[PDB]
Image (cartoon, rainbow over all chains, first blue to last red; front, top):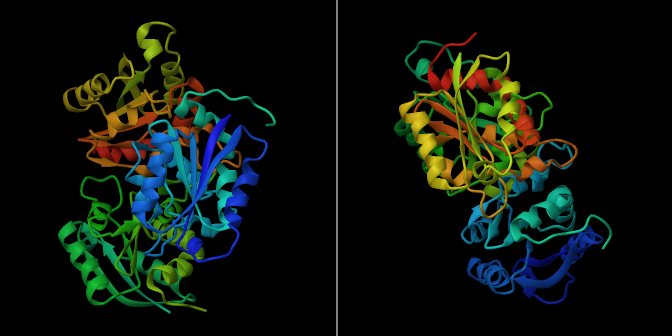
Length: 163
Length: 159
Length: 159
């Protein structure tokens, strides 16, 4: 059982009424697995602010997994990967590759995500794309090895079954 | 559409030891697509010369896409990736992975290409392998998402 | 005929808790190929000790290929990638990708290996995962292009 934080990165999340549907898509993928969503926040497309939350969640809250979504595109404003890399002690390129659906012949556009994956302290951090469909496919691609990955990073155990 | 620059990097080709037929393969791949070759150049495996052309096409000419080919192997002098990375604002690893044909059941020689992919200003730059065959397969691998990637980097639309 | 060094990185094996059977799997994969294992070493998950052997084999022994196994995972003690990367003149990301078995329909546990691949001087170095299964499967993935890669890196010819 691993504590997960979902961070939705966009300035559009501070412009009034809209339901964060990507957040919901992510929860669905995790449903049933050794995961418990212990945090959820919206943050602007401002590296300083993204880093403050990631820093807080890893260093103080001690979350096991942080799934950010959005800001990984080719647009000059998408700087989630850069902001994240600067906070990582080491990266896990294999997970970044899985999120791009490399060699799966599933969704070609998924290859454009610059999202990174890495560890800070005892917290695994993955940058998922910003659309509901994108975040969903990228997370489902890593799901099979996510519990094993988290057990190594966090040193915490997990049970193979329904939760 | 998008203006493209093709930069062939080869010591042998530059010194006239052999002819460049790779650009010919690249042109065919682009034919029929929202691309138009605005420039072509041949330089040796020398970072200083590779960069001069990259800066020129991106900063002066403002080309939308730069496709280099060659100098991405494991040979000591193959230094196109290093030269290119020095000029990029940010990289797009997904495209570099596509050019290495990652995922094929049969381990490809393409995996030996150290080519990178990235953005400088509003120009997308891709390092394709130097062989005609290699450059073709690598370019075809990215073609499906090339137009969209370019629209995102340049801001220009296509049809 | 390329000279190979096998470096096993394992706290347990170094402590003598359980013997190294991974080198056996590696040797079997290379059997029948233009390879001769000239050196074997066993060290714990300690960067200084890992670097010491890598420098000795690349700089003093002149080995052509170094295959390390172990210490590439996500556990806090796994630092083979860091220790290795810092000694490389250049990286060959395509080989690191092949070792992660990227592209399998079923997400592989190999995706959790942070092992790198690169060149130091005229020596090609690859970080394989630590289990017999892990090292075996990752090495089989790169085997098809290994002789070619070494010929380019070492300058030594190969049919």
